[PDB]
Image (tube, rainbow over all chains, first blue to last red; front, side):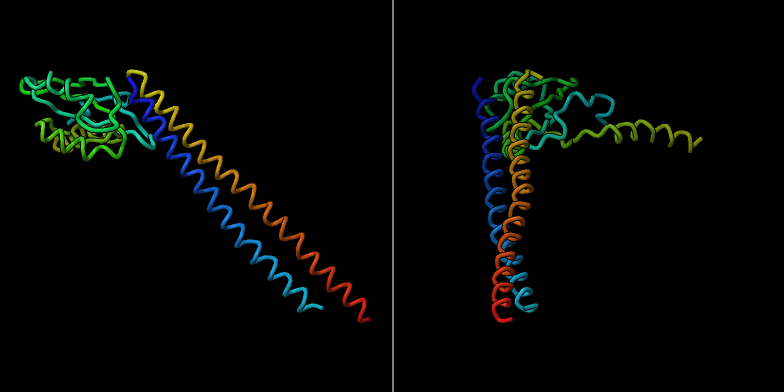
Length: 49
Length: 109
Length: 56
């Protein structure tokens, strides 16, 4: 009967959405990470020179 | 005490999304519950009932469902006079209950 | 057991694997973000080096 296919598709769709949310949160962290690193090191390079 | 009845194999265990419940049903209401099994709440696993015990007034049976549906299931079960027994399997507690009555008898002696 | 349960367990396994693969993507791409930052800071270093050589 159809309901098992619906349930499989439902929980795999929750994983599709959870995977996409992890991918989105990953991108947002990388946009913070490079900002912290590059600006700190640029300022240290300037404080040195 | 259900440790005299149930086995680890009678349940879905450690799932992220499924739970197996125990329902106690009046013996005259057996065919009504068999008719309701497919329909009583959303996201129940079809055609997967199993009677684990039976008695003069009633019988005790499996159902398995998506973990969201448990409240609708137990509520609509109570509206149909089917009774969801609160139980969760852990073999260490089943073994502990089998040990304890013998310990109590030993300590009394 | 009725076999439907086994297919839903396979689906929850496929589901868990999809979210695990997104965590594995995050773990790899974090190192890529560090390697990108490490390129830019060398340009700022080279720029101040060339400017300092010009002043000397």
